[PDB]
Amino acid sequence: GPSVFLFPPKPKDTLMISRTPEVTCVVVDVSHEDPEVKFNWYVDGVEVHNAKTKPREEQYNSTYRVVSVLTVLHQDWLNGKEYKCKVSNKALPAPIEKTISKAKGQPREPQVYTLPPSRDELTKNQVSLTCLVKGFYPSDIAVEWESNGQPENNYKATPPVLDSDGSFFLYSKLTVDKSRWQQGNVFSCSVMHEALHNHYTQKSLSLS
Amino acid sequence: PSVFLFPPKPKDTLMISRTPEVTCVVVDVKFNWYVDGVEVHNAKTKPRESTYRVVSVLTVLHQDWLNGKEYKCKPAPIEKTISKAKGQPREPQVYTLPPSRDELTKNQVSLTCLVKGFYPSDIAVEWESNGQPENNYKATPPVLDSDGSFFLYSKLTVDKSRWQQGNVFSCSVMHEALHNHYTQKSLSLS
Ligand SMILES: *[C@@H]1O[C@H](CO[C@@H]2O[C@@H](C)[C@@H](O)[C@@H](O)[C@@H]2O)[C@@H](O[C@@H]2O[C@H](CO)[C@@H](O[C@@H]3O[C@H](CO[C@H]4O[C@H](CO[C@H]5O[C@H](CO)[C@@H](O)[C@H](O)[C@@H]5O)[C@@H](O)[C@H](O[C@H]5O[C@H](CO)[C@@H](O)[C@H](O)[C@@H]5O)[C@@H]4O)[C@@H](O)[C@H](O[C@H]4O[C@H](CO)[C@@H](O)[C@H](O)[C@@H]4O)[C@@H]3O)[C@H](O)[C@H]2NC(C)=O)[C@H](O)[C@H]1NC(C)=O
Ligand SMILES: [Cl-]
């Protein structure tokens, strides 16, 4: 019989009102002999109709894959509403239902601190710019580096880490060529989190 | 009944004064122990403890473990084999970072130890001051960097007054690619 997987929206899509958060319901192992699939979508028990279901696509193991995409309201997701995808198929004894919702917890506001390279690293060709984000809850977050209106993507974040007061922290490390740091270029750490005013704050870093 | 074989704590393998051990835990009893096939006899088996658990502890030689030797613990007998994670060692660089000026508003400040460029991921990072291990720090797990080496960050939280008073804090790093498997970097207001 078919199997169902329900995927949440990207955190950043839920946090930035201009972006498009979606819940995605995927169905696999749909047989040739019972190929039709019906999706029903519910937000807190109430059925919604606006979903966009894609036509079935045959896989290399002669089974079909069918995907339905529900556009969500940012506030609905952040208010903890449950999204249910019910999948119907004639090979199933009963319809398969899957429910998901935002991680629970009292929100806490992160503090964002930029830290320049250690003097000892200035011997090297590349230097590390550090963005400490601490005190946030829950763990869903987006941390990004940029300079002069361009994303800097030679960076890596640690996963969120549980701190001694029950909040999370993480560190994001931006690696840049030493000359760029010495030349006086401004680098910025953008943090996106539900407990921030407007879900956004930015802290900048440049050589003195 | 099932068998679990646990490696030594990385720090025990790295500090020659410490006592690294391989631990063979059997749950729900004879033990045979082998180092690269060759049987060894020095293991110390504990007495048993609504199912029984029995544990045998083998003392290992630091250099044997770091040289990649395999440790084997034994309807039919169950065998389990373990050894050190493989990979060309790379030396970590250790950098201490003081608190951001913006955090100096707060009652507690964050002291940061960046350790980067190390391989493999086994490591020990610890904070201390005035001959005492510091209370209240947390490290991130190792993270895979864009050049294939790992990095991590260790955050020490201290009261602002301690930072302002001029107290020295030290980040100790223990890793196989370091000379003597040890390096220390200090951080203070001055
Ligand atoms: C017949 O074929 C179909 C189709 O498969 C394709 O075609 C075939 C022919 C072949 O070529 C395949 O190679 C093709 O892919 C088969 O369909 C597959 O069926 C699987 C179930 O049997 C199903 O597996 C499940 O996958 C779940 C989803 O997780 C996977 O995908 C993630 C993608 O990311 C998503 O989520 C993140 C959020 O974190 C989001 O950012 C993304 O945008 C996206 O929405 C992966 O992240 C994830 O992990 C991979 O990647 C990470 C790194 O990111 C890495 O660390 C991992 O090692 C992985 O590589 C997954 O891969 C998954 O949740 C689910 O788990 C369930 O079960 C476990 C227990 O095992 C349980 O603990 C969980 O709670 C959970 O309930 C499960 O693994 C495949 O998704 C599906 N394939 C497709 C394309 O839809 C079909 O099975 C087959 N039939 C046969 C042989 O009979
Ligand atoms: Cl020692």
Image: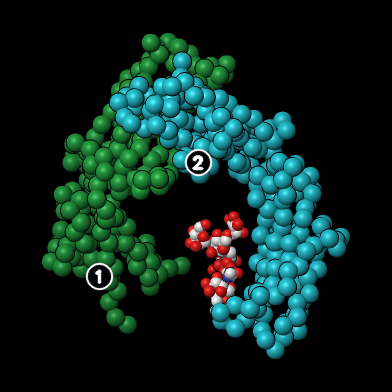
Chain colours: A cyan, B green
Question: As displayed, is residue A37 above or below residue B165?
Answer: below
Amino acid marked by disc 2: Asn
**Residue bearing mark 1:** B74
Q: Between B146 and B44, which is closer to the camera in this rendering?
A: B146
Q: Given the image, what chain letter belongs to the residue carrying mark 2?
A: A
Amino acid marked by disc 1: Lys
Callout 1–callout 2 Cβ contact below 8 Å: no
Q: Residue at x 30, y 26 (%)?
A: A123
Q: Quadrant of the N terminus of chain A?
A: bottom right
Question: As displayed, is residue B11 above or below residue B162?
Answer: below
Regarding mark 1 in the picture, which secondary structure is present there?
loop
Q: For the residues marked 1 and 2, what is the alpha-carbon distance in whole angstroms?
A: 49 Å
Q: Residue at x 79, y 49 (%)?
A: A73
Q: Quadrant of residue A32?
A: bottom right
- Residue A153 numbered tag: 2
Residue A5 picture location, percent across and down: 65, 67
